[PDB]
Amino acid sequence: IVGGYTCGANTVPYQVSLNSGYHFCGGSLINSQWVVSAAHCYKSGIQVRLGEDNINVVEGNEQFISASKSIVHPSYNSNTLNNDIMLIKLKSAASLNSRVASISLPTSCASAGTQCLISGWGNTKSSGTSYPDVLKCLKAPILSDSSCKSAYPGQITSNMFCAGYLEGGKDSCQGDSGGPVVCSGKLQGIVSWGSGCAQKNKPGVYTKVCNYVSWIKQTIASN
Ligand SMILES: *C(=O)CCCC1CCNCC1
Ligand SMILES: [Ca+2]
Image (cartoon, rainbow, N blue to C red; front, side):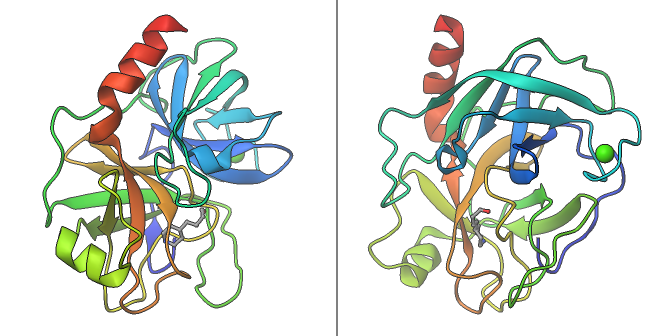
């Protein structure tokens, strides 16, 4: 996250770190046995780390659970990143409480101007790499579809939305992929792609979760 602040330990209880010997993507806990992340974060050998703040030190509250299966959306397109969403089932259920809790799925989509919270352990520099130890947060608004399409002509599908600042300086960045975009207590987006990090006129693009609620519910119910 570039231009963000330190969230504070366990203040984002649904945030998870996907680990393969190092942190490579974020995710969101939606129930005790399932996490939602981005399809482009897929790989085998994923260990889900819950209740984290400093990802390089065991501080207490951490729960490390292996993924039993990962389900990439059947229509995911790696070239356009359309349908960039994946579900991960945990080998055992997580222990929920105040430091580890699930986030609710939306009932309606959010409108332009809604302020959301984006969090993650991704790069904090737009020009070069600096990865933080603790979780960073950023408050960002959802932009209008016209500003989003004017920024990325021909690349925005109806399963994506832009959030951020056109002036540059504040954005999600590499390492934040797969993580949550929460607005009014509902998971509305997943960090997906953008051009560089916090560049002027190039906001971040997020997977529009409200378009997948029935798919998520139906997939969880059958697995
Ligand atoms: C995931 O970490 C790949 C890059 C994610 C982009 C970075 C720029 N802001 C939008 C998300
Ligand atoms: Ca830790």
